[PDB]
Length: 233
Length: 242
Length: 9
Length: 9
Ligand SMILES: CCCCOC(=O)c1ccc(O)cc1
Ligand SMILES: CCCCOC(=O)c1ccc(O)cc1
Image (cartoon, rainbow over all chains, first blue to last red; front, top):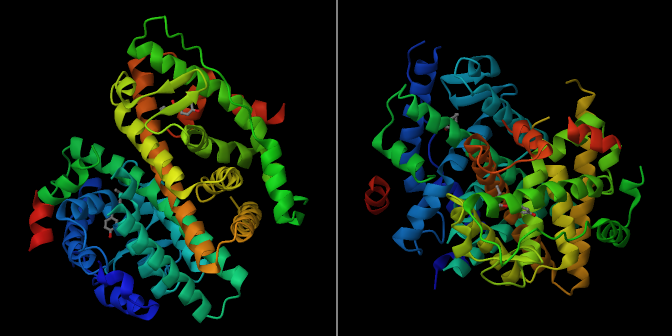
């Protein structure tokens, strides 16, 4: 039996809030394809180390076997980087806040080949979140849902599904707590979950881009990032 | 619009009424099959299904409210997800098998025929199993399929004008959510259960998006290999995704 | 586009 | 794999 399931909504929220990884910085050098992609993959690689340690703190995650933990992170890592990026960029309409000192716009996406398309998707998701007034507490639930959900069908399973339900309960809890009517609660739940489909889409496209970028042997990729990428076959 | 004026029961009715038919393939158990014929059966079938899908889309509440360019976009984005969810729905009562057509039931084994089609097969079977585990109802299925059509391209669309197009879709989407909840409430689910099941259903859409993306790349691969025949409509859909 | 056509007809 | 080691560290 997993401790995750015994937690109350408030304990779930606090656990997730407390597990949050930090906002990392990029280089303090005040844009080519090589230079931009170099910064992004460097940043990604550093964020991945934090994400792996963040995931271990999502309730229910460590109760899984190591092999299942690897499977879920392998499936979800880019989605998780992306939703985090989108969340960070939410208060910056028209910009992607990769780091506090790397706040980019559509125009710079044109510099990397096949990047402006992904950029435009990221920006629209960010705008969507902003217009929905997405809250930090809702954000952390959504992010953990991605971690547990994305690889779950390419599979215990019940456990993951019970924990997923627990996070659903937690989301509704927050929406009730914010004073939303019943109908507003279920409509908002649906709206947020449907965005996860778009995040999957963006991850799939980003993965293709990363692969071509790997093949073009343009920027070096860490052995970690290469292993995470290779997992998507 | 009539769309936003529909009760939950009327919405279910509309969607059920609009269901396309189940088509037959050209499979012949006596004929020998290659990689390029088995796959040819599937693409021939998909092409024929697309024509019915287009006409089904027109009968989804709200959809013809949209500009022609926006209808085109939504279908270009969603077509393979919609084909895939229908396949998974048909295959629900056949564990371990995909019912591409009543005369074309396939095994994982037979799915190895095409180069790398195995992974996609497994994903579809996992989804089917998931539908079985949840005991997905036909009424819930038609709601999800219409959600895919309306949702999947909604964030990849000019002016503050073309923004109101996106806003009508969100209103219709909310209405379908209401319909799902109503169905669950009538099935006797508690409120906690309603919300949990709604989430479970919507999270499956993420896996369907994933399968569609994977299939889209296998499709592009097949194109270039030019060994398996692809129809002009299918080719154009493919291109919409680049 | 075939699709655009079929959507009209 | 590196992930295995990091998940354990
Ligand atoms: C492959 C196109 C860019 C995809 O996004 C990233 O590379 C990225 C890196 C760090 C993040 O926090 C988010 C996204
Ligand atoms: C790229 C093809 C992946 C497998 O799915 C199909 O070919 C297909 C054809 C007709 C359907 O109704 C569903 C799937």
